[PDB]
Image (spheres, coloured by chain):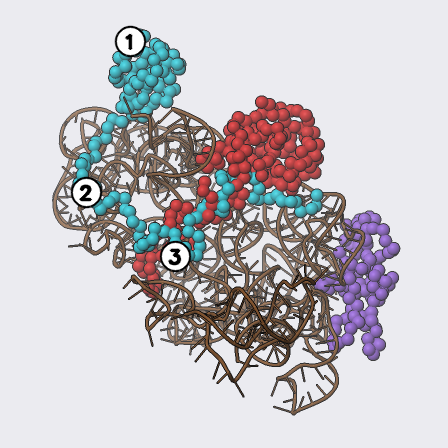
Chain colours: A cyan, B purple, C red, D brown
Amino acid sequence: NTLSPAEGSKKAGKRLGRGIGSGLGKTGGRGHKGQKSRSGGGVRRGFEGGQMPLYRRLPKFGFTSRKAAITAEIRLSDLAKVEGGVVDLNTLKAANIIGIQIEFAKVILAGEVTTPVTVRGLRVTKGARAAIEAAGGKIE
Amino acid sequence: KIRRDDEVIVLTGKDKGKRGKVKNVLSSGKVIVEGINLVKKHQKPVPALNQPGGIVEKEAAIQVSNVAIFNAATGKADRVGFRFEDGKKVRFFKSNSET
Amino acid sequence: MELVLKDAQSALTVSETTFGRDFNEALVHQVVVAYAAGARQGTRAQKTRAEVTGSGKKPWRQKGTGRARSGSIKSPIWRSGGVTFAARPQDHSQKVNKKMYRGALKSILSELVRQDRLIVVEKFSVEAPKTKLLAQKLKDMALEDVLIITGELDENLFLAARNLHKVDVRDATGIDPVSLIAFDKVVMTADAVKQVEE
RNA sequence: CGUACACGGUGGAUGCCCUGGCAGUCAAGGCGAUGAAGGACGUGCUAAUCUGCGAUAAGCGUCGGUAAGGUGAUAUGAACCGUUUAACCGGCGAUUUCCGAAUGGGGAACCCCGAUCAUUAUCCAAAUGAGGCGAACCGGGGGAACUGAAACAUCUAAGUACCCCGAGGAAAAGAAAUCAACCGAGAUUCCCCCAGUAGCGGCGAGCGAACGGGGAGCAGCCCGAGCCUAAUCAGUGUGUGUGUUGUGGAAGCGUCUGGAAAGGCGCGCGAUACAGGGUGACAGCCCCGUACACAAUGCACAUGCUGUAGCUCGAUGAGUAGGGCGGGCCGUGGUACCUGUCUGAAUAUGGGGGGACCAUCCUCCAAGGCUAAAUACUCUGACUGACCGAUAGUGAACCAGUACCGUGAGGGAAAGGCGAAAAGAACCCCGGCGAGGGGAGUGAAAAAGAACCUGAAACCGUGUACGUACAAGCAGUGGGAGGCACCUUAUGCGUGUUAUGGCGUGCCUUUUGUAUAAUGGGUCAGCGACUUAUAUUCUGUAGCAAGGUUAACCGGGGAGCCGAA
């Protein structure tokens, strides 16, 4: 009625996670108290991202290799057999999670169920020769 | 609200039952009605409170709480005086609910 | 299953809807414990611009100190300054989410499909201009004690109920676990549920 | 004279209030030589300030609104005006002395005239322009240092600070001799992403794009001739959506406390209107106001229309492309852009470009020009804010940017509140006395009297409790003896305080060691010292699970990132 409601306005409802004391948590409350790694803690931080060095000096270093074709596109068996049907060459890959702006890939028999759909790909490895041969089809 | 061009009727103060027009209204809430006055020293018909001192305000200092204008309820009060050129106010005056 | 909806006349049945998610009363209550008023300016450690001023300007010996709008910050030896003892870059909270916050945002939606809880109301509810009509639809609903809980809806903020006992009006679009259940309890509408589903 | 307390004072904290600030948001947005902004100085019967005007001087006139009350803030005395309807509110008009960027000339406001540059020119200043101001934003030029690289000459901070010139309310850019995943995209900016990748760097530290994609906004065209009329130009008529104020506007109810409720308690109500304020103490239903309604103005962006007026043909810009020398600058690498000196093409049966040079493809064609739309700030108006509260907050809620300081530039405070009204101390005594008050009066919740609410601490006076001019010092504790004083906490149970006796070297940092002749504080209150983006690496909790999460922008996305050999 016209009585001041027991409550009801802003901070009503659920919150975030575990019983949060106050706002996001602090470590060194106001005033004075240890809080630190002791010693000469001030001027500037310790680490730098590298070293001194002794491990970074001149170990078994190497060098920056030229950009690769950026092949390496998982096209494992199954997930393509128990999916769709035939015709799965260079034209119907977007439907699947196989479609890199670059090119090339590979087949990794994750399963063994027959399909026996054919698949081009433009690549080939062990197992690739297997299947799609004893089941039918031609790779390229 | 209360206006100066209206009549008031006391109901509590020792001046209970007295009738008169509103002299003036202060931003204090008090209202002096033509009638509720006091007898000064040299017996001069001038409204004022009853207390010893030097120079003090006039008016009997009445309160809108114990007065009686147009109270929408069952009371012992009766008729009360009340602009007209307004027109719209005439309608409310004609209604037994407001003025 | 099938959550029965209610019309303005708090009919026994109308349409149906529901949500699927393992309700966690421990987690939902673990939700009503984090920010009812928890976005009232924290006190972190390392979260802003802060560009040195170098030499120049006004003559006087002074050292490098955090200066934001003539206001000192990130400087340990000054209100709101660097916290050398890192880990806890803010102000006293609780040792604690990606799954508790959101996960609860889901679990809560499931709290509705529970018996001893709220009830779905038809869209016509948002129409009710007056507030008294609500108190009535809440009385006949046999849930007038829900005012003791809270209230919600869909579309726009239902003003006509912003006065009812405990009512933090909110829209199904952007409903943080907060409005979802004021003090582990709530009440919504039809269109709301649908909008919240997604 | 030690200590506690009591009464009064000093003082001013605190509690409450606050006509103020701080911050965010929406709307709106230029002024002037028809001489503005600002300043100086006048003006109300008295007025010293502030504000409003300005010599018709806190005012005059018209229309509309409004209304009986009015004559600014100060509620004073005197006094005036208003129904020949004022005050007040909005718009507009009239007037508007002298000085004043004024420019005739000089000049710290005073005295006499278009000064200076420039165009047209009947060369007569005759007809015109420039010469100033304005919060930031914007464009075109000039261009550091400290600092960082824990040295420093490249580099970095900087292309910043600052300086010069200029436009608008918006500028700059721009229709491609481009891009270059391509049988393709295809004007230019801006936002997000792509990238912190390519690239640069004592390759040390650091520095740091673009193409493309996703969006916002979309408009293309003009320089010789032929011809003819709807591009363009000139002019005319002239908006829909509004600005402020007033009108259609419900509502003291009951009991109790009180001088009074906006109290407690009981009951009811508003809501396409669940801001706030005022009214004698916490009234959303007392008043204004909030949603709402109507009328006065400005803007009227556009459109319509008249006369102009299509369209057609060819070409298309050399000291340029390019090369060499010396520099600036850029992420620019022999592969950015620009300046200076010198040299110097061809020409579409030509030439340039696709991040190296030269012959062969694809694309596109400079050395001429113009071009709407998409974000900024915040003076001004309004609103809001889990912001602060008058040693807080803007320096300024009280005369404040005032008092006051400095030759000057410049610097720069403190001071809030009695209340229902008015009181704010009448009258009497004393005394040298309008400078010392008993008494008494004022009062509500003023434990009120002219810097007045409340009103503490340091502290002062009187007074009380108790020691006290042989007295040894942390000044306790336990045990046993003494007295005195009080029986609102009756029970061989406690206090105030003290005589006497056994013990007992303030507090805080530096330092191997500090009670120490190591350092700091006379005391007090207030004030005063560990945060705002992102990235990386671990830890505790929790949902779910090789799937998982999104970022710009949409409750949709999955770009992209990490993981999966």
Instruction: Choose between C109 and D58: the one closer to the eye.
Output: C109
Mark 2, secondary structure of its residue: loop
Mark 1, secondary structure of its residue: loop
The spot of residue D454 in percent (x, y) is 63, 67
C-beta proximity under 8 Å, tags 1 and 2: no
C-beta proximity under 8 Å, tags 1 and 3: no
Classed neighbour count for the residue bearing mark 2: other residues with Cα under 10 Å, few (<14), some (14–19), many (≥20): few
Question: Subunit of mark 1?
Answer: A
Side (left or right) of D255 relative to D9: right
Q: Which residue is mark 3?
A: C77
Residue visible at 53% across and 35% down? Answer: C26
Question: Subunit of mark 3?
Answer: C
Disc 1 vs disc 2: which is toward the camera? 2
Amino acid type of the residue that numbered disc 2 sits on in the rendered structure: Arg
Residue A57, numbered label: 2
Q: Name the quarter where the N terminus of chain C is drawn.
A: top right
Residue visible at 49% across and 32% down? Answer: C103
Is residue C170 something that shows in the picture?
A: no
The spot of residue A13 in percent (x, y) is 56, 39
Amino acid type of the residue that numbered disc 3 sits on in the rendered structure: Ile
Counting residues from the N terminus, which is met first, the one under dot 1 or under dot 2?
2
Q: Which residue is mark 1?
A: A133
Residue visible at 54% across and 37% down? Answer: C29
